[PDB]
Length: 341
Ligand code: NI
Image (cartoon, rainbow, N blue to C red):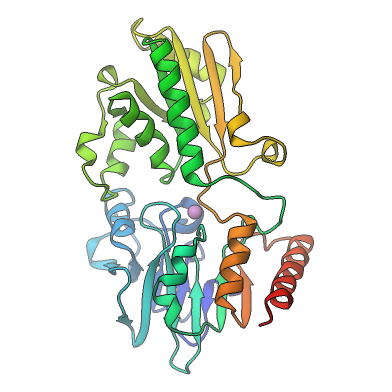
C-alpha cells in the first residue's frame, strides 16, 4: 500500500509510486527520475499514464520497454495542464533527466515535490521566485550537520589532475571508473577529455548513455574497449580482485590501474580535505574514493528551505525511524526560528 508522503492531496496524482500495484484513485503517475528505488515496479506491462521529463521517457521506452502510448514527456520550465491541474517541471540538479514538480492545486494551495535534488542558489531564480509554496516534499538524504562535502567542480578538478599526472608519469597506466546507475557522468567524461580518449564500456551501459541527450556524445564514448584508456566497470568490480581480473583481459597493454569510486558522503569527510585525499594501494593498483554528491549537503538544504519559507515540510528520505524523524523536525524548527517565517 502506497504511503502518504507519495500522494498529492486534492489530485488524482502520485509521485514515485510504481511498486504498490494499482493505487486507488490515481489517474496519473509522476516519475521524478530514473533511479531504481523510484521506478521500482515499472515494465512493458504498465498501462497507466506516466508523466516525466524527455530524458526519463527515453529511458522508460528503451531500458524498461514501457509502451510509447503511456509515456507523457513534458518540457521543463513550462506551465502544463495535466488532468485539469497546472504543473511545472524544474531541473533537480541530480542525475540526467531528474526533476522537481510544482503543483497548483484547484483550491489555491501550491506544493513543491523536490524528488531527489542537490540544492543550488540558481534555483532561487527559476519559476520558484514568482509565488508562495505552502507544502514542500523534501529530499532529506543528508539532513544533519555532519554531512559536509566539496563542490562538484572541486571534486572534478581533483580527479582530472590526479588522472593526468599518473598517465603522464606512466603512459602504460589504465584508468577505471565505477558506475551502478545513471548520474555522475562528469567524473568519467572529464577524465577521458583530459587524456584524449573515448570512454570504453559495455553495450548495456552505452545504450543507457545514448538515452541522455548529452551534446556530442558520439564523440565521447565507445563499446570498443581496445581503443580506450578510460574504462567503465560496475561499482562492484572496483576492488583489488576485480581490477586484477580486468587487467588480465587487456592483452598486456597496461601495467598499472588507477581507479575511481564516486561515493556519496563517507565519514573520512569529517576529517580529510579533498586536497589531502589518498588512495588505497596494493601492488600496481590504486583506488580513490571521491565524495561526488548528487544530493544537497546540510548547508545547501538549509539555505534553500530558509529562502523558500514553506508553511509545512514533509520529508521523503530517512522516514523509517523515530530518531531520524525527530532529528529532522528539530532542524526544521531551528531553521524557521532563525529566519523568522
Ligand atoms: Ni536518486
